[PDB]
Length: 168
Length: 96
Image 1 (cartoon, rainbow over the protein chains, first blue to last red):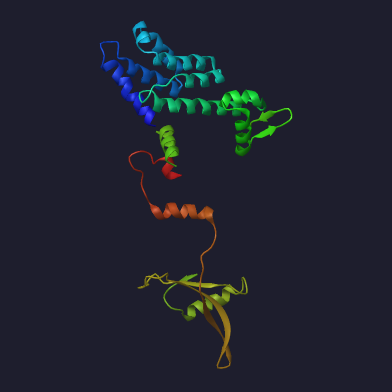
Image 2: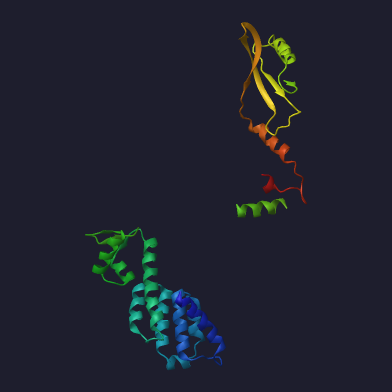
């Protein structure tokens, strides 16, 4: 909602404001905004446009690109460690908050379709919270957990225009 | 059926001859001289009634109803409306 507007004003800003290389905070928000849409191609291309000058100047930006390298592999546990690695207050946090929750939803959603049966330890990597916390949650939602083996199972107006058209 | 204003003897004479075809025929009378807005057809049957001890053929009036025939009705629609085609041919949607 709020984020979509924030990409719009920022997208405008990249072309309009600079002499061709814009300042380091603007590029960081923009990169972070591309990850929320999960438009990873344009993200990657964003980093490749970025000169060596911004990479020395700004390290935060390079952290935002690292989450994204993993999103390309689609390896979940790896995503989570990188979210914790870097923070940049104000300028990165509201959009970051959204990134973390967009990948968890993507992960739960992915599993629900993907697997008719999955190991609970693998599932623990996907949501990214330990085994005790996960097994407690799945039960409430209404998914079945098997214990001993520890496996988890996911669960007129048109017509007149058309008649008018054919008769003519 | 016959034509004319109120009931008269010349209708009763003809109704006895009709009694030869079927023993109980209906009589119907239409006034096209009607000064009145309601439906000016009135329906009768004949009764044989004794007056002053002599048996007389006298008429008795019946009320009416409306009834079936959808096949016939769709023609009464066309007959009733008397509408003309516009600029085209009249539309398929319209007619349907």
